[PDB]
Each structure stands twice: as structure tokens, then as C-alpha cells.
Image (spheres, grey):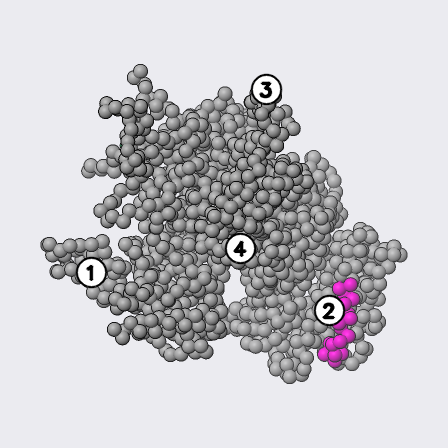
Amino acid sequence: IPVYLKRAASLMRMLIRIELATVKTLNITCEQMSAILDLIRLQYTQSLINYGEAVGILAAQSVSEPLTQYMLDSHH
Amino acid sequence: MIDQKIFETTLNIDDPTNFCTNVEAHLLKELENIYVGKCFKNSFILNITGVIQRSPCFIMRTNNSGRGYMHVRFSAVVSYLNAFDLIAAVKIIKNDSNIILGESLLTEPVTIVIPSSESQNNVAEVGQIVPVQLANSSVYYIPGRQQASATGSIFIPKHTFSVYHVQEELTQEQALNLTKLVNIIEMLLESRSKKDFKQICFFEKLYYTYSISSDEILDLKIWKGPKGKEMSRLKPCNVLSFLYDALKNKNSSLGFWARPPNLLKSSPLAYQQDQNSFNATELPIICSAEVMFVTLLKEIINYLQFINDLCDTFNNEQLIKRHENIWMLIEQRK
Amino acid sequence: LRLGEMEHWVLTAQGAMQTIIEKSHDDSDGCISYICRNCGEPAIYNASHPIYKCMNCDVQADIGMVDSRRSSIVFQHEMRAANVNITSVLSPRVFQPA
Amino acid sequence: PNSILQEVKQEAELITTEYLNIKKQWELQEKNACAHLKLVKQLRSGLQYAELLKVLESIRVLYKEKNNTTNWNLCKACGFKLLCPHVDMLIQLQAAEASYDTMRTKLMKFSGILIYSYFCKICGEELAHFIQED
Amino acid sequence: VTSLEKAGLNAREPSNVLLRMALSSPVQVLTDAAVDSAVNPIYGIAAPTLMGSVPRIGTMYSDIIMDEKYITENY
Amino acid sequence: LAVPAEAPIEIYGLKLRLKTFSPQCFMRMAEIGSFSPETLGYVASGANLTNFIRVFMKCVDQETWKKNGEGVVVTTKENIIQFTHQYIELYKFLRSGGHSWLINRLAEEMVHRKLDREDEPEENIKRVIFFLKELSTMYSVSPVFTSGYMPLLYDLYRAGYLEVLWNPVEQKFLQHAEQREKE
Amino acid sequence: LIMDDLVEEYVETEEENLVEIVESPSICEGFVQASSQTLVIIPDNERITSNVLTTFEATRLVAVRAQQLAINGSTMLKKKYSSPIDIAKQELFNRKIPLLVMRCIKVTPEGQKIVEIWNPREMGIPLLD
Amino acid sequence: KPDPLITKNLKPGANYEKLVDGFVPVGTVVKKGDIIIGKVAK
Amino acid sequence: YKQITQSVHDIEGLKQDFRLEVGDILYRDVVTGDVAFFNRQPSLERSSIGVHRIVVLENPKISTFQMNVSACAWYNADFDGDQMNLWVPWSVMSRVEAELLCSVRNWFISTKSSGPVNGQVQDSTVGSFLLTRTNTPMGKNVMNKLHAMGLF
Amino acid sequence: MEAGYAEIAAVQFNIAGDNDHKRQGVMEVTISNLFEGTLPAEGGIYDARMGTTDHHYKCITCSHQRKQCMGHPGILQMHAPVLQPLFIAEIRRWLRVICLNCGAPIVDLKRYEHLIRPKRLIEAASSQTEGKQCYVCKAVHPKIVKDSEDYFTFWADQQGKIDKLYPQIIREIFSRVTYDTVVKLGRSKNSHPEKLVLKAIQIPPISIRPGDINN
Ligand SMILES: [Mg+2]
Ligand SMILES: [Zn+2]
Ligand SMILES: [Zn+2]
Ligand SMILES: [Zn+2]
Ligand SMILES: [Zn+2]
């Protein structure tokens, strides 16, 4: 695995190790743990950015939209 | 000359799902419908041999039609005529306005315009099949056209000839390359036998620089058959044997070369001299053995094909009788 | 009725296409451009009247069908009117190893 | 369909008999195999304008009657619809390399009846359009 | 630290002549491209759009080919 | 230097530039496939494929000037006549039928040579696939199995019924799927 | 004498700051055609792109299939649907779509179009139904 | 009011009726395709 | 658009066709359930263009583009004179994309703030408060069965 | 036939010389007449070979109607050369760095053989070079003066000797520049100064001048 991809999963690894700690998963069966891990994998896959996204235009819109509100408080 | 060629093209597929289920066959059918019998990329393309390489059927991206295109790399049989090519069957379709049109009836569909300013022309009429030699102007293959375009004239024995001085020896690879033209000459000589002897004799007498004694002396047939006419001076050499034992490294091509009018313009005969005994009015062309051998072999191929096509088009005496001016001007310029 | 710059930005931010295509070509001045692919200049192609020619290199004409808009053709003509030569390289043909 | 028939009195049987006649005629037309079906397809599928006149003459071979401008033409080998008279004039003008305005003026004999388009009086096909004159 | 003005575009995408013409100052960009014999690869959004084409992103980022084997074996 | 058109210049010698081109240039030209045999032969002579230019022109070398770039330079007048005659013959040969055949065969052979040189599911997952096999006959979830069964989970997400991963259910919403398909 | 339709003279002020030898051969000048590419398909075990279709890829597959069913219509689907869009969506969901997804990873200078070919019938589908 | 011989370009789908002396009279309801004010050139 | 003639035919000239042929192209009216692209200028957000299911208003006296007030957050719109552009995709690819990629359900979560865009606005917020409050000035906030049913 | 599907991958920008105009021109403008009745006059600026903008005639060049015709450029053989309006500054830069007698560069090419290519000519023209002596023909480089009355006229100032640099004289000067000088000054071989003077301008297709720009 490339190093940057390992760092990309650091936050999710942290969250999984916190919420799936042994103290927190005492009333969960092994098959239930498999289902939980499969659901986590599915949700992580569903959250990835699509290939060919115009993310630059998305960022331009998302940063230019607050600019009119920043103007609206120019007298403040 | 008829030859193979490899082309690159992009087709258009209006039914990509139906175009599949048989890709090679549909591809071949589309290539035949598009490129067969049409000038394309400095050649004519007579038939599609097959597809060498091809692309996946990509779906068109810049429109909402759903069609595919696919890239095709196919080998095709093409005809590339050149200057001084001899076409023995040209049918004149126009004679007014001093343009003198024509149309080759051979395997290579070239439409040949013939100059009218020259006093030699203006003797053929509409519907008159007569041989034509292409001028030194390069054939004009307009892409997508159903025939080639060239300028030619009524063929004349053309007593002017060239002398080739050879200072570079043949190599093994060059001789192997010349073996292809040697094989072409061999098939031409093989096909020379099928044509009836009297017609080939009459035509060869017609298109000869000098005069031969009423087409009865000797039995010129080449394809071995060691005969010879005129014999103005010196001994011919068999170019086929010279190229065959050239592969065997038993000879040297260094010297002077020429194919004078006294030689039979069809025979595999040439002079390998060392003193330029020929009385041509031009300096020897210093070149390599490959250049001279290629030039001589192409001349032999052109003349052999010329004779074969002449025998093919005029297969009876009715056509010979019909041409009321073709056969006597050629005998006039002797 | 105009679909301006910002509408195109929104449509391409959604990654749409096929709607930029529909509106900007099929419901607009969208046309077909022909390029020789050997010189890159606009070629002359006509199916009905048999015309497959290139005013540049003549026997080397290999006309490709390129989806375009009349606005872009006019824009390139205007650039060439100011003595700026516009040459379209065209995507190379890709072949699967047989 | 029922309520349409009770609220129609002998004409009610004419409606549902003509309906069956048209349905069978249309099924026959869908299953029709006159030799023109490839010929009319070739005529409209854009080919060289020299070949188009030859194909249009080939269609004229199967003409049942010389219809200047009255109604459709029928496949002589099958009796079904063959070619509208406007298509003959239109193909004539295409081979003549006539202009769009010339075609619109000449085709202003099949004009029926903002659309901006003229439609055939016989087959209801788009003859030409007139939005603005330049 | 490049800017979001014309200078930043010139520093980041000097070869994208069409994009820089579409942003601002088309006459100077065109003149400099003609003088410098600039080659403009077609990428992004502005350059394909100015050429009458569609950007190769979104639905067009990945191309589609026909599954010839599957079509032959399942007509 | 460079002189304008129709500008009187005084010819003391004539140098032919023996331009050298890589074989990839000839290969690109053959791939384009529409070039005339004269230009094809000229470039092939530029590369080390044919030597017709050097064959025709090295006989009138008379090297007396050098100046970097490789070529032949003729100084004496008779050498100029010989140079011109050899040039005319060379370029007539390059446009001749024989060299046309040779260069077309060479381009063919090179292109042909280049082208011919080119060329077990886990127990829970087993149960889930079994459930989807029954569901495929009644919902558009035609199952396939990969290593991570990611398409399997994606199909269990669109239809709902993600609960089969941890709960026995299966038959609970199988009949619900029957009712939905019937409706 | 009074003209109203003025043209508003246009000014550009920020100048750009972009940062043997013979006449020309038939190689340096010309050859705009660009050399043909060979399709280097990455082996299935060397592929690094996602085994799940993106919404862009799935949408494009459905659109292409439905447009093809508009002109064609020979379908391998079992249940009959009255619209090409529904037919294409069910073909994708039933893993019967006859299309493939090519992801062009890289075009090399040497003339190779390195691509990954993905089969949508063995891929994850993110669409709704 | 133009006539079929006056046509050369008559608008498709237009009415060309309701025109009295080249103008639609006062008090006449006019719809989308109706021709108000008839003018002919040449 | 008849395929056999490769040309467009008026519907008033096709009175003799009975049915339609395979490969024909029919240009039908917009009906309820069709997808349409809704756009308000200036188009500044990723949700400035969205796809809505068409509800055809058969009242001939209505000329406005009607929308739910909770959908206005996508377009930063209000009903005080704002004009919006609506075009119905007619091609198959565009319709597929409209119902698969550009539907407003994809813009419920903001691309900018990563949070929800839509929700209760004005009367709906006050109504939720009034409905969920424990007491009214009239006593306990309760309704009988008839009025509880009328809420749904 | 059968123009295959294609996509534009790159666009090349170049200075269009008169040779390019001659190659690309489908017709040569020779007359001032606009229309011969209801049809364009042949050889005029409205000639149909340039494309059709009216329904009243087809193209001729592509045999298409108005909708399907993209327009085709023509040629006007100028009796006297003209300077390219977009590249007047390039003409000025080239005039100040090469000798107006033999075309040799008056500047030292080795001096600028460390800068980037887009800047070599600018810095070469930045230097004065007035009164410099050519090392080939021993001529004195004049002062290249840009006329303040218009955007194109150039003046040759030889220590007060004032003579107008006509486009014909400029073409004679620019035609003596070698491609070696062009390359060593950071310019492409497609940017030879000989293309900056036009004896055959391109009249644009009628598609971009519909029936004012034709006046
Ligand atoms: Mg408002
Ligand atoms: Zn070209
Ligand atoms: Zn009709
Ligand atoms: Zn045109
Ligand atoms: Zn000097």
C-alpha cells in the first residue's frame, strides 16, 4: 500500500479502533462483527470521490458562495 | 503496378451491438463497401486482403447517438501506376475540343488525357482501344475517386535510350530484394506462353524501333528460348541468370549497362560493357548495381505486361481491322 | 433563452455531459467538423455530392469526423482571418495488438 | 371503446368493421414484402446524387399511375403505398443541386392546411421551413 | 504562491492557450501563441469547449467499449 | 546568409546537404501511408535504409570545402555539370516505377514487421449468496462473487435487506420481495 | 452629425509573462498526424482502479445501453419494460449489460495507451432502484 | 391581403384571414398564428 | 420522425398511419413524471441546476413554475418575482443522466458545507413547534382522533 | 469516403504566412462586384466558393446548403505587401536585431545563449544597436523609428537620413534572415520573420461575414 494511502485511512482506523474496542464489543457476536465490518467497508466505498469529478469547480463554487455573504457584512 | 498495401482508418458503426456477434466479417464487409475500387492514400485499392490490427468498438463520446467507430488497420491489394507505364487498352471517350480523353480497360482504372497539341495524336476516334504510354508526370490519385488520373500519349518505340554506369557492387540483401522482381518476370514469361504466338509476333513487330523482316525470321519467345533480332552490335546478356548467380556470388556487376533499341523491349537481355560502346546522346548514369538492375527489371516487366495485355485486348483480327490508324503510324515512325 | 457560463459550470460540476451535449449541440448550433488529420486543417467532406478533399495536402487527405459547434468553427475562422494558423492534431488511432 | 359505441345506430357496426379492416390492412403493410421496401429505403438513405436519380427511376418503374399531384403512389407488385409525389420532385431538385429557397418555392404545391415548417398535403412530411427571409 | 488572476494561470498552464483566451485578454494570448508556435493540448473544460467539443470528465471521463465476447456468446 | 527571390548571386560551388533522418521518421511516414514514393525514397535515403542519394551523388564528391554538415560539394565547372546531371538522374529514378516499387515494398515490409512484432465465500457470505440466488429470480440482483464481495454488499444496499449479514431473517423479506414483485 | 452607436474601444493592459539548422525537413515541420497508439491492457491482477462502478460510469453505461436499445432492441432481459431507460437499468442490475468500461490510466510518449478494462457485470453498482 | 400567387414566402401555419384592406378590423380577436397587417413587396 | 423516409412528419398529415413503425421517433407532450432541469440564475452552487419530476398543472390559468418552498434552498430562490429556467431532456442519454445523476436528491447534502440543504422553513418550523409543544394556551396540546387523522 | 469519427487532441497556433493563405484559399478575389443579380458575382468577396450564407444558393466548394457549410477562405493577391496587424511588435523587434542590408544579426547571438527561448528576441531588441556595424557587409544599422501617426509605419533613421520602411522593403529585409538566426533568437522555424509580410491576404469565409464587416 502506498504511504499516502495508509495515511488517508488513519482517521477511519482511529475511529474504528475506538468504537470497535473490546470493551465496546462485548455483546456483539463474531458474525455480527463481520456484518459490522462489511457495513463499514460498504459505507467507506460509497463515500469515495468519483473518477472524473470536476473538484476544482466544486471548490470554486463552495468558496465563492460564502463571498457574497462576506460582502453582505461589509458595513460591519 | 498491382501491389499490397497497409492502410489505417476509422470506421463508423451505426449499430454497435449488431455489428458485433461477427466482428471480422462485418469489418471486412464495411471495408469492401468503403475502400474497394476507390483511390485512397496515393493508391487505388482493388480488394481488401484482411484486417491486421483493429481497435475495440469504442462508443462515440462527443454525441448522444450511441454509435461506435473502431479503428481498423487492414492490408489491401492496390494498384500504383507510375510514369512510362504501358497500358495496352485505352478506350477514347472524347475527341472534340482538342482534349482527347480516354479510359484504361486494364486491371488498373486510370482515366488518361492525351495531349492534342501534338501532331502525333488526333488520329484515334471514340470507341477505339489503343495502347497508351503514361507521360513523366506522376499519376494523380484523388482520394475517393473511382479511377486514377494521368496524362499519356500514343506509344512510340522511343529509340532514345539511357546508359547506366555501375560503380557499386550488388549486396546479398539487394539481390534478395530483386528476386521479387525476378519472380514477377518469371510469372510474366509463364503467362507469355498462353497467348497465341502470331499475335505476340505481330505486336512485337509493331512496337519495335527498327524493322524486322516480315515477322517470319526467328521465333522470338524469350522465357529461355535464346533468339534475337536486329543484333546491331555486341552480345546480349541474360539478366535473369545474372541475378540468379548474383545470389551465388559468382559474378560482378561492375561496368557499363544499357538496353539499346536493338534489344527486344520485352526480353531479359542487356549489355554489361566496360567502355560505353553505345552511341547514346547522353552521359552515362553513374549509380549502383541495384539502381540499374531495378530500372532494367521494371522496364522488362512493363514491356512484358504490355505485350500480354496487347494480346489480351486484340484477340481477333476484327479489332485489328477496326483500328484504321493505330497500326500504320507506329510503322511510319521506324 | 441562454444557458450561460455559470449554467455550464454547474452542469460540469455535476459531471453531467450528455446534457451539455444535448443543449449546447443538439438544441444549439452544434454541427460536424471535418479535419484532414494529416495537416490538421478543416477538410471538405460531402457524402451526397462525392467530395473527399483537402485544400492542403491533396492525395494525403484522411478526413476525420469531429463533433463541433458552428460558434467554434466561426471562432477558428476568425483566428485564421487574423493570420493565426489553427491546426487540429486530432486524437491518434489506437490499435489492439492482434 | 364500449361507452363510445353505445353513445354512437347502424353506424356503430360500420365503425368497428372499418376498424378491423384498417387493422388487417396495417398488419399486411407491416408484413408487406414488395421489392420497393429496399428501394424506398435506399432512395431516402443519403447516397450520391447521381445514384439517387437512377434509384428514383427504378422506383418509377413500379408506379401504378402517373400522379402529378393528387395522392400517394402504389407498389405495382403489391398495391401498397410506394412513394409520395413530393418525393419525386424533391429528389429531382436534389439532383439538380437546387437551392433551399428554390426547393421551398417548387414544393409549395404539396403544402397542407409557431411551427415555422410547411408539411405535405399528401403524406404530411416536412417540405421545408420558413422562419425568416435573408 | 501563484494567484487566481491571469498571471497565476500563465504560471500554471502556459500551454493552455484556449483557457487563457477564455479567461481574459484573448488578443494578446492569441498573438503570443501564434508567435511562439504554441501547442495547446485539449484537456480540462475551457479548451474542449472553445473547440466545440465536450470536456472528458464526469460521464465522459471513462469511455465505453462493446463486450465483443459477451455479445457473440449471448447475441 | 540568405538572399531574396530573384536576387543576383554568383555561384562558386554547389553543396548537396546529405540530410540524416531517423528510421522512426520513415516509419511514421509509412504509418501515414499516403506519401508519394519520391518523398518516401528521399527520407529512406536520409535514413540508413536506402542509399540511392549517396549512390548517385558520392561519385562527384570532390571534397574541397568541408564546413561541418555532411554532404558533397562541387567546385569546378565540369564538376557542376556532372553534379547537375547526377541530381537529375537521381530524382528521375526516385520518381521512376522501379524505385516506387522498391520503396513501397520497403514501407510495406517495415510496417508488417512492426505489426507482427507487436503480437470461496465465507459461511455468512455463502448464506447471503444463497439468499440472493433466490432473490435473483424475483429482483434485479443477479449475484456474482468476488474476493471482497463488494458488488454483493452493493446489491444488498440498493434493495434493502442488508440485515441478512447479521440476522437470520432471509425468509422474512423474501416473501416481502414476492409481494413487491407481484404488485 | 450625432452618432450614438459607439463601439467602446477595448484595451488589454496586463502583458503576459510566460516562462547546422536547415530550412525545414519533412519531419520537424509537419507530421501533425501523431503516431498511432497500441492498446496496452493492464492484466486483471495488476489493476489498481476500483472494482465498483462510479456513478458517472454507471450512468454512462445506462445511457449508452438505452440509446442503443432505442435503435436496436434485441434484449436479453427476462421481464418486459416499456422504456429503454428501464431496460438498460435492469440490464446493469441483472449483470447482463453488453458493454465494457475502459479506464485509460496513461498515454505513454512511446505510443502506448495503457488502459484497464473492467467488466460491469462483475462490478459493484451504486445506482438506486 | 396576399394571395396564393402573392405568396413566394407565405408564413407556414399563418392565417392571412381576418384581413380587410390589409388590416385586421377593430374588435377582432387575434390568436398566435393570425396575420395582423398584411404587407407585400415587389 | 419516420425512419423509412429519414424525415420529420406532421401529426396532422399522419391520419392514415393507424399505428407507428419500429424505429420511428415520436415527439410527445410533456407528461407528469417526466424529469426536467430546474435552474435559477445566477447559477452559483452545484444545486443551482436540479432535476425534478414534472407535475403538469392542467389549470389553463396557471403560468408559473410551482415548487415546494423547501426546494428553494437548492436555488437560493424566493417567491417575490424570481424567474427560473426549465427544460425537459428529450434525448435518451440526457434523460438517463437527469434521473440518475442530477436529481435533487443528490443535492440534499451540500457539497459546500457537507450538511443538509433542505428542511422546514417558516410556516413549517413554526408549525412543528406548535404541534410538538407540550401545552397550548388552551391546556395540554392534544387532538381527538378525527383531527389526528386529518393531519395525515 | 466515410469520414471516420475523430476527436481533437491538440491545437497548434502559428503565424499564417502568404504561402498558407495560397494553399488554403479556394478562390482568388479579383473584382469589386458583390452580387450578379440574385447570385454572388464570381471572383468577388461574396463568391459562393467561399461558402453560402443564403438559402438562395448552395456553396459550390462543398456542395452543401447554408446549414451544413462551414465556409471556406479565399485569397486576395495584394499588389503591394502589407504588414501583419497582429504582429507589428514582432516586426519592430526583428528590424532592430538583424542587418537591413544582408540580413545577418547585428547582435551577438552568443550573448543571449543562456536565456529562455521566449525572451531572447525581446532582450536582443531591447539593446540599442543604433550605429552598430555589420561584420559581414560593414553597414551601419539605422535607428528603427515607429511612426507615431499610425500603428504600422516604420521609419529608418540613418543619422538624420529619413526614409520610409515600406512593407516591400521590410519583406526584402526579412527574407535575408536565415533559419539559424531565427532559432538562435529563441523563435520557432514556423515563426520566421518572412511570414510577417503578406502579399496575399486571406478574405475570411462568408460564414463569419453574413450579409458591417464586408464594407
Ligand atoms: Mg427574489
Ligand atoms: Zn490535409
Ligand atoms: Zn408528401
Ligand atoms: Zn461550403
Ligand atoms: Zn550586413
Residue behind mark 3: A23
Name the residue at 52% across, 72% down: B94
Mark 2 to mark 4 CA distance (whole Å): 67 Å
* Disc 3 chain ID: A
Asked where in the image residue D105 lies, by quadrant, the reply is bottom left
Cα–Cα span, label 1 and label 3 = 89 Å
Mark 4 crowdedness (10 Å alpha carbons): few <14, some 14-19, many ≥20: few
Q: Which residue, given by chain and number where applicable, does mark 2 sit on?
A: B304
Q: Which residue is drawn at 11% across and 56% down?
A: H25
CA–CA distance in space, label 1 to label 2: 79 Å
Q: What element carries label 4?
A: loop
- Residue beneath label 1, please? H16
The residue under label 2 is which amino acid type?
Leu
Question: Could you tell me if the residues under marks 1 and 3 are in contact, i.e. CB atoms within 8 Å?
Answer: no
Say if residue I130 shows up in the picture. yes
Name the chain under label 2. Answer: B
Mark 3 vs mark 4: tell me if same chain: no
Image coordinates of residue J152 in percent, x first then y, are: 40, 34
Q: How dense is the environment of label 3, judged by Cα within 10 Å: few (below 14), some, or many (20 and up)?
A: few
Alpha carbon of mark 4 to alpha carbon of mark 1: how far?
Answer: 56 Å
SS class, disc 1:
loop
Q: Which amino acid does label 3 sit on?
A: Val
Q: Are marks 3 and 2 on the same chain?
A: no
Tell me residue F11's x, y (percent).
63, 42
What residue do we see at 70% from left, 76% from top? B311
Magenta stretch, overall SS? helix
Q: State the image coordinates of residue I79 (x, y, percent, origin top left).
A: 27, 34
Q: Which of marks 3 and 2 is in front?
A: 3
With B267 as the anchor, is J118 left or right in this view?
left
I139 or I1, which lies in front? I139
Highlighted range, magenta: B183-200
Give, as a three-letter code, the residue at label 4: Lys
